[PDB]
Length: 112
Length: 116
Length: 48
Length: 41
Ligand SMILES: *[C@@H]1O[C@H](CO)[C@@H](O)[C@H](O)[C@H]1NC(C)=O
Image 1 (spheres, chains in turn brown, blue, orange, yellow):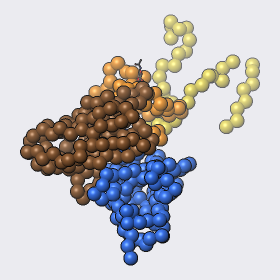
Image 2: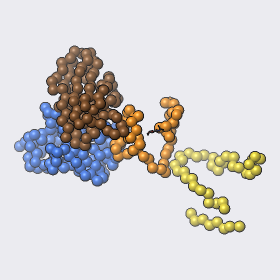
Image 3: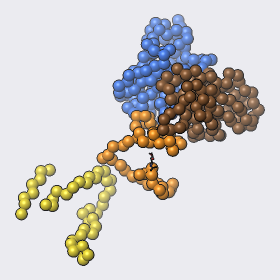
Image 4: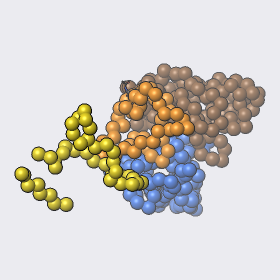
C-alpha cells in the first residue's frame, strides 16, 4: 500500500510546448542489483485501455517515442514532454511495481 | 502480434456471480501469470490482484481481499475472474495484463453493470 | 559468454546459436544492471 | 600424419549432408581400452 499522488489539475498547454508534470512516489522505490526504478508510466486515451509509455522509469517504448525520459532516484519521477501532439492528448498514469501491493495514480489530463 | 480478447461484457444482477474469461493469441497461458485490473470511471485506476496458471495462490489488493476471486485455467488459453456482492460502485471497466515490467496488453474493456 | 563477447556479430550477419542440454540461468540476467531494454514478447520475464 | 606418427582423422566423410541437426552429445571414450566389448542398443 503506497499512496501515489499525481498532478491534480489539468495543464492547458499550447501545441508544441513543454509540459511539466510529476507524481511523487513514497517508500523510495528501489531494487537491489538493478538501479532502475520499478515505476512504469502509462498513456491512456478515451476509448482504449492504457499502454506502457515508459517502464523502468527510463525506457522508450516503441511507437510515438518522443522523449518521455524521466530522471528520478525513486522519491520523485518526471514525465516532461517537449512537444504535445494529438497522440499526446491523453491521461498519464504512473504505477509502482517494486512493492507487491501496487496501486495506480489519480491521473493527469493534458490537452493542446 | 499478441492480443488479449476478453469475453464481451454481460448484464449481471446484484448478489449473483459473474465469470469473465480473457483469451490470448500468439502464446499460451502456461508462461503468463496474467494480472486483472478494473478501472473505476471518473476515478483513479486500481489493481485487483494476481493469479498464476499452476499453483495460482492468488493475492489481491487489500480492498478486494475475500471479494474478488480469480482462477486460472491450465488449458483453453483462458482465465476466469469471479466476483460477488456486486454493487453500484462495481460498475467499472476491466482489463487484462501480461505482467511485464508494466501491464503490456490490456483487455478491450468490460462494463460489469449491476441493475434491474 | 554470449553477453561477454568482446566483438558482437554484425546486425545483418547476426549470429544464430542453438543451445540445449544445459540449464539456463536467468537470475544473473536480472541481477545485472547494465541492461536498459528488457522487453519480452509472448512470455513473462519472471517465469523464464 | 608424419609429425603425430599416427592415423589422425582428417575430416568427417561419414555423411554427405547434415541438414536439420537437432541433437549432439559428447562424453568420455568407451571403445578404446584381446578384450571383449559388449554393447546393447
Ligand atoms: C557477462 O554478462 C553478464 C550478463 O548476464 C554479466 O552479469 C557479467 O557481469 C558479464 N561478465 C563480466 C566479466 O563483466
